[PDB]
Amino acid sequence: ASCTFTDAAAAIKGKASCTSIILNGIVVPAGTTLDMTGLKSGTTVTFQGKTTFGYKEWEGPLISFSGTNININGASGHSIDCQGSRWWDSKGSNGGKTKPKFFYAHSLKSSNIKGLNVLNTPVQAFSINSATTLGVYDVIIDNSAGDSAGGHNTDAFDVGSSTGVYISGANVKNQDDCLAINSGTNITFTGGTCSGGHGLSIGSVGGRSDNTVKTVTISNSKIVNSDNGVRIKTVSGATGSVSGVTYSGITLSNIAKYGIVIEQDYENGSPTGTPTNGVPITGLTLSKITGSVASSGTNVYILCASGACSNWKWSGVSVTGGKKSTKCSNIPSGSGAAC
Ligand SMILES: *[C@@H]1O[C@H](CO)[C@@H](O[C@@H]2O[C@H](CO)[C@@H](O[C@@H]3O[C@H](CO[C@H]4O[C@H](CO[C@H]5O[C@H](CO)[C@@H](O)[C@H](O)[C@@H]5O)[C@@H](O)[C@H](O)[C@@H]4O)[C@@H](O)[C@H](O[C@H]4O[C@H](CO)[C@@H](O)[C@H](O)[C@@H]4O)[C@@H]3O)[C@H](O)[C@H]2NC(C)=O)[C@H](O)[C@H]1NC(C)=O
């Protein structure tokens, strides 16, 4: 590589002069970002050894990348260990200590992240925002320690205001969404394994600067020991759009709350029981969605406002083991969808 750094400030000072960078065993000073924004176009950046971070109660990000034609890779043996248990307090980003976001994959164009091995994020892991064609391959996010040490709001991939995001072969163990797409166009999640969290989610959609989800493929993935399997949420009273979404080849195991949940009634982060019509869900395909829900959970819950869900196609959906909801509303007729 042009440049190998074991020091965070040296790396930040020198980055734009390096065509290839190795970040080797960096201890990132407490309360600071490993700031890899503004890279020279075409730069490759490789993590080696164990990256760690000083402790401070602050908002992060711990790491930040931006640029065009950037490749962000992990070397054999590397890890990025945030030692999140230092912050974890069962309250996540909703109270207790101020806890830093981990990785800002922001303003990355025609770029790729491959093979990053991430452990113990304080709260959310990857924030993907203002990205234009970004591959995210074979990323491992292991927040399993958080199950018994107070992990909360440890989402793996949060996506907004982005296009052409392609997440492939992710392996996630956490306590919140495996995926949350709040907005974006041409977003893929495929070949993934999601354990311990809240499933593969669209939304909540609405009430943000960007409320459009269009052309999404979430496929060939396993969801295990999670609250939800397939999830789409839209915000009560909001305007937006969820269209051209396909979930296919999704296996579910021991889902606690909902195998499939689609509801248009989110207000301040909680369902109201009353759906609203300003964020229509159209062109929704579910194909080959199979598996088990806990007896105390619910197989399928569809809570559409009148006229607000249409052009759905569901086939090979076999979700069993939980209760059958008596509360579903306005399911697209003839779609094959059923609670
Ligand atoms: C919706 O989102 C998706 C996901 O982001 C968008 O799909 C992505 O689009 C981008 C372009 O914007 C693609 O990047 C390009 O990929 C081209 C093809 O790459 C692959 O093929 C290469 C060649 O394959 C063969 O050769 C190799 C040996 O060379 C063999 O080993 C192999 O078996 C094949 O026989 C592979 O080498 C490579 O690893 C990929 O598998 C590239 O050719 C292209 O590179 C061009 O530009 C580069 C400058 O950045 C330059 O270096 C190159 O020379 C070349 O000019 C570029 O990387 C993504 O691959 C693609 N991702 C996926 C998953 O599809 C999609 O476009 C978007 N939809 C819309 C409507 O926008």
Image (cartoon, helix red, strand yellow):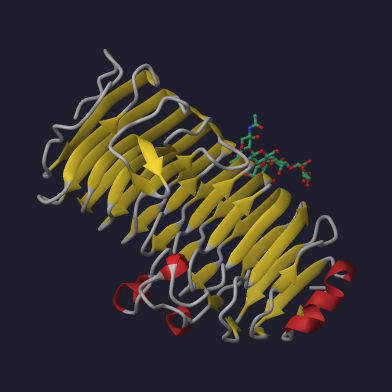
Q: Is residue 77 visible?
A: no
Q: Is residue 228 visible?
A: yes
> Is residue 198 placed above or below 272 in the rendered structure?
below
- Residue 31 falls in which quadrant of the image? bottom right
Relative image position of residue 218 (x, y in whole percent): 43, 39
- Tell me the quadrant of ligand 1: top right
Does 329 sit above or below residue 140? above
Residue for point 52% across, 78% down: 82
- Give the left or right position of residue 66, taking residue 317 as reference: right
Residue at the image point whose x is 52% and y is 69% from the top: 117
**Residue 283 placed where, x, y %?**
44, 21
Please indicate whether residue 172 sits to the left or right of residue 254 in the image.
right
Q: Residue at x 34, y 79 (%)?
A: 149
Q: Is residue 136 above or below residue 165?
A: below
Residue 7 image position (x, y, % from top left): 74, 86
Give the left or right position of residue 37, taking residue 193 as reference.
Answer: right
Q: Residue at x 61, y 72 (%)?
A: 75
**Furthest residue in direction right, as rendered:** 17
In-front residue for pair 39/99:
99
Front residue of this view, candidates 98 and 229 = 98
Q: Quadrant of the C terminus?
A: top left
If the image is split into quadrants, where does the N terminus sit?
A: bottom right
Number of labels in the image equals 0
Residue 257 x %, y % = 22, 50
